[PDB]
Amino acid sequence: DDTSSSINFLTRVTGIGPSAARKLVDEGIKTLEDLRKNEDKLNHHQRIGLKYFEDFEKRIPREEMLQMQDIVLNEVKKLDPEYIATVCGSFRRGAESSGDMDVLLTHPNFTSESSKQPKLLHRVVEQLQKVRFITDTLSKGETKFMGVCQLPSEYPHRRIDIRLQPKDQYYCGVLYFTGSDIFNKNMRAHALEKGFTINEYTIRPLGVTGVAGEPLPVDSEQDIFDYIQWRYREPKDRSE
């Protein structure tokens, strides 16, 4: 019990997985105090998770999400109008509150046949840091950024992810990350009944063989619904 309750509290800190949590409790750190007195035992991601432990357990009001959206979309547009940025998650479905901000980013210069273009993403991250919206980085790779942001003022720090997706796979991504999970499940099931398979990257025909063919052209979410003969489903109507 004691061990379990300690392992559960730790897992509430972003970055601290189950294994990492056990190893930590196994070393004598169980409380928030212990953690805060032992940052030297945590990697960068876990340490930032600890720093904003409380803030990260707070919900985000839609009104704030909207202000966050404006900041993101506006800065991106200034860097290059060709950039396309979409805030997904339950927020895109009209949710009155969110737990984090998930942003899908693309640029016509970056397609799936293209090699890595990390600066496409990092340029955006750097600018948002410049305007002081992004305050910390949990981690960042060639196509994904996980960090912390804050509205200027008192405002809680919020979790934000920015994913760079190839232009030719962008809308399948926006669809997937908009959800909900139930809706995605139901849409993929229907796609199958129609001879198509859909994932977060593409929609492909499904030969009677069961083996998916080449990816089909997608230039909007609408195209995906069109392929499977479903009338367009507004994000607000995608609870399931």
Image (cartoon, rainbow, N blue to C red):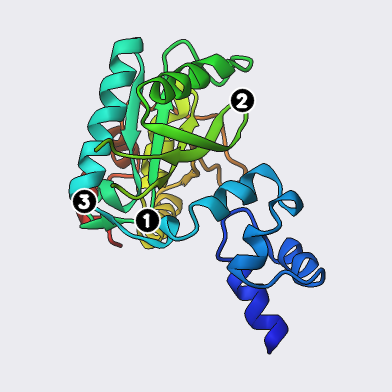
Circle 3 sits on which residue? Answer: 62
**From the viewer's perspective, is residue 205 above or below residue 195?**
above
Q: What amino acid does circle 1 point to?
A: Gly
Please report whichever mark, 2 or 1, sits nearer to the chain's N-terminal start: 1
Say which residue appears at 34% left-offset and 38% top-offset: 224
Q: What amino acid does circle 2 point to?
A: Glu
Say which residue appears at 39% left-offset and 36% top-offset: 103
Circle 1 sits on which residue? Answer: 99
Circle 3 SS class: helix
Query: How far across and how far down the image is residue 115, in percent?
Result: 63, 15
Query: How far across and how far down the image is residue 134, in percent?
Result: 42, 32
Q: Nearer the viewer, mark 2 or mark 1?
A: 1
Query: How far across and how far down the image is residue 205, in percent?
Result: 49, 38
Quadrant of the rendered image containing residue 108? top left
Please report whichever mark, 3 or 1, sits nearer to the chain's N-terminal start: 3
> Spatial distance from mark 2 to mark 3, Cα to Cα?
30 Å
Circle 2 sits on which residue? Answer: 142
Q: What amino acid does circle 3 point to?
A: Arg
Circle 2 SS class: loop
In this rendering, the count of numbered labels is: 3
Quadrant of the rendered image containing residue 9? bottom right
Residue 217 or residue 121, whichever sits in front: 121
Query: How far across and how far down the image is residue 46, in percent?
Result: 63, 51
Say which residue appears at 26% left-offset and 57% top-offset: 97
